[PDB]
Every structure is written in structure tokens, then in C-alpha cells.
Image (cartoon, rainbow, N blue to C red; front, side, top):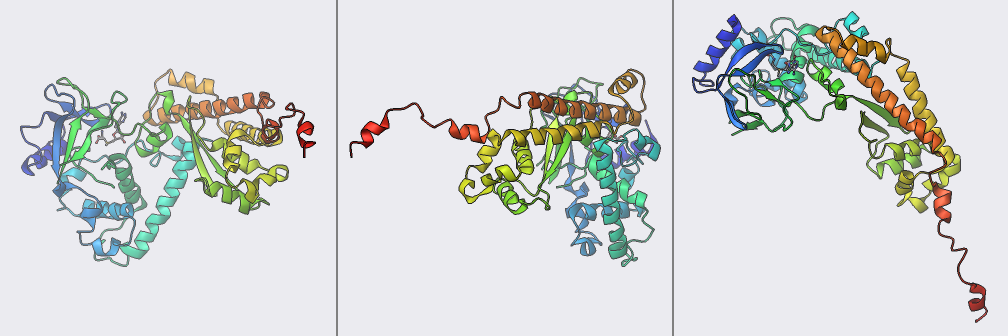
Length: 424
Ligand SMILES: C[S@@+](CC[C@H](N)C(=O)[O-])C[C@H]1O[C@@H](n2cnc3c(N)ncnc32)[C@H](O)[C@@H]1O
């Protein structure tokens, strides 16, 4: 199989973790290293368990030499350091484990500059940059506020690579369904679209991993890393994406600009209804628009004419009105805004959707494959969004705005009330 692997398997045997009782062995798979069943495994059948003596979470670090200095650092920042540190120490408990970890994955955080060019204009790139940058800054501070000031605790130098490595290890290996825990044995299980349950991680302590599917002997055991992540999200978190178009999403960022002459009132309406000065709306392919997006768009586009809706008089129905549409100029404005944003965004890519689809038809490198897939999907969402609002522009007169809704109760054709009035 492999040196480090064979050595790693041994290490788990003597640690009492794995035994000749476990129905699975390590194997080289297209997804790297994975867990191949040694015998017909059944649904919900536990395949392996690990002693909390082997975790690597905010509970292992704090109980370590650097626990004191990291006591004030965010949980992840704390674990990254612990990971890097334990990596160096040629005696650490995670010696053989670290020997197995990949130097890299296909997460966009490791992509070269050429590789990233393949994501030109893509939201995924904007996001990966932000995340890389932010992690960078955050990690430098830890070098000058904890790494250097404590040269006793952090011997060997800590390169920016070491950071991204550890950060990567967190994003693609840590289990969040329980925090951030790392489990040497259950770190090898891979992801599959075949698993549609997402009920595997569980501890009795002891981390117990149960196979959500019946895997016949020889086959690989899988799990569902997350039924809710977009492809953009899997691309950055792990090094892969799915062909499932239902994973393509594009998030829109709305906000009530402070320069808005009705900023104070608008923000008041937004917060009274669960929305901040800045709100993010994730838009998934083939899914209906997220609730609140339209009403918020209408709020953003409001305008002097319909500003009367911001008066204390409607501070109990204003949101309902926002949901039912304000006025034609309001709707026309917001549609114009969204449509221009889509066109502008779409124009930011360096390939046409046809080109991407043709590319997908050949053999693509894992990273190029991710870029192509991601960018095509984003374009599908950008175009679907734009299509939705294009239609809306056409139906711009089918909506019954505020003024109309207000007169839908005049009772012009009632009784000859004057008769009754002249009766006193
Ligand atoms: C939790 S680790 C899995 C263990 C990994 N296979 C190894 O060799 O150690 C997750 C990483 O494995 C790979 N992986 C897992 N599921 C995959 C899939 N369905 N397709 C491609 N790569 C996958 C990715 O690089 C991902 O970031």
C-alpha cells in the first residue's frame, strides 16, 4: 500500500483504536486515501471508533503548553497553531498521522496564480482571495503576538504555507456536526453524492463513525460532507465539486447605503424584520428566490415618492407591503439594478458557457475541472437570476402595488348612504 499508511495503520492498532475487529482498511482511491470495506458493511453499521485521547480540538490545545497563550484566540486560530507545532515535534502523538496528511488538496487556497485565472470574474475567486487574505493577516498577528513573543513555545519558524496548510487541514477534515474535532481514523472517509442522509458523525469519550450506506466488500465507504453547501463552498472547503447543478449557487449582497437619505428609517425597518444593514442572499440554481430578497431590494430602492411608507404609521405592516410590492417605479428600479448587476458580472468571465461545456466534455485536470464547473454554474445562476428579473420587467403592470391595493376597498358602489344620513 504505502510506507506512512502501513505505519499509520499500525499506530492505530497499538493505540487500541483499530483492531482485527474493524471492517475496513485503508486504500489508494481516486479521491486519495479512503476507507475500503473488508467485508459487506450494512447501513448504520459502525465501521470505526476513536478515543478522545486522539482528537485535536480547542480541548486538546488548551490542555497543552500553548494553552495559556492561545486562551484568548479564536478556537480555529488556536487549533492551527497547535497543528503546526505538533507537526514539528518529532515525538508528538500525531507523528504517524501527520505523516499521512497530504501536503495539499485542490482547495482554491492552494491554487497557483495561473490556476486561479481560470476562475476569473467568479464569485469563488473573490471569496477565496478574501479568505486567503484574511487568514493571512490573522495568522501574521499570531506570529508577532504569540509565535515570536514565545520563542520557547514555537521553536522552528512558521511559514505562511504552514498556516494555509493547517487552515486547509481544518476546512477539509474537521467534523463540525456535534466545534472543530479531528479524528485520525475517520479522517480518511470520503464524500459521495450517493449518500443523501448525512447522519454519520457521533460519539459515545469516543468518536464513532457509522456507514450511512450498505457497502459490499471491496467497495469504498462514503459519507455526505454537507447537503447544504454550494459548489463554490465545496471547492474552497474541500478540493472538489459535484456535477449536480442543484449545487450551483451565487450569493447576492444587499445593503442599505449610509448615504441613503432615508438610511435611518430603512435600517430601522430592516432590523425590525431580521435584516442587518448588510444582508447576504444565497441564490441556488433552480431554487426559488430566498424570502426577504425582494422585500429588501424594494426597501433598498425605495425612494422619495414611497418614503411615506417609512412613517411610524406603517411600522407594523411596512414589511408586508414590501413583500406585496410598493410601486411600479420601485419595481422597475430594482429590476434594472439586478439585471445590470448580472450583465456586468457575466461580462467578467473570460469564457462563454459554451466553451466551458465543451471543455467539460474532454479530460480536465482536477483544478481546471473545478474552475470550469464552478464558472459554468455561476453563469447559469447569474443568467437564471437575470431571466427571472427580465420576466418581471414584462409583468411590471401585472403587480398590484400599494396605491392600487389601497383602493381595492373603496366601496364606491354601495348604498345610497345619503338617504340614511338625512335621517338625523
Ligand atoms: C476528509 S479528507 C478525506 C481523506 C483524503 N481522501 C486523504 O487522502 O486523506 C477530504 C479530502 O479528500 C478529497 N475528497 C473527499 N471526497 C472526495 C470526492 N468525492 N471527490 C474528490 N476528492 C474528494 C479532497 O481532496 C477532500 O478535500
